[PDB]
Image (cartoon, rainbow, N blue to C red; front, top):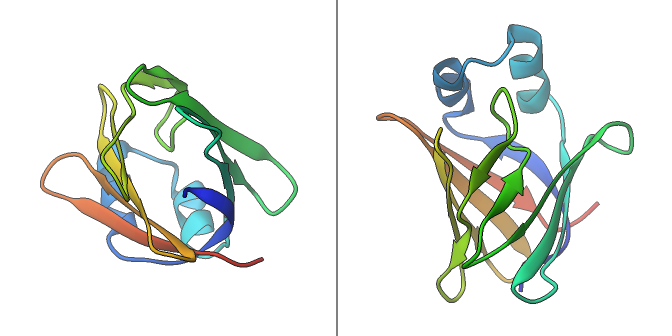
Length: 127
């Protein structure tokens, strides 16, 4: 489905995965001590993903799968990357890191990747 409100309740290897990307220490501590809210609307091959900071800033990741698009990402800057799908899951690969999302009924989880490190998360489906 990939459609609904979600929010990051917890993380697994976020700290190190960040230390590889190279994020600022305060911003590192925020996401892990903060519920980044996450909405999604899989409107067909195009998606309207979003990553709200609880109403204030809103970063967004609109993209089209089997096509590619510019995506804002949690790295230093925007990149362009080929999002793809499989069946009950989602796929992407940027010239920077790799990531695959995977809905579970009423829960969004994601698993990022880059160099011997991988950051799982569990954006639950609630508010």
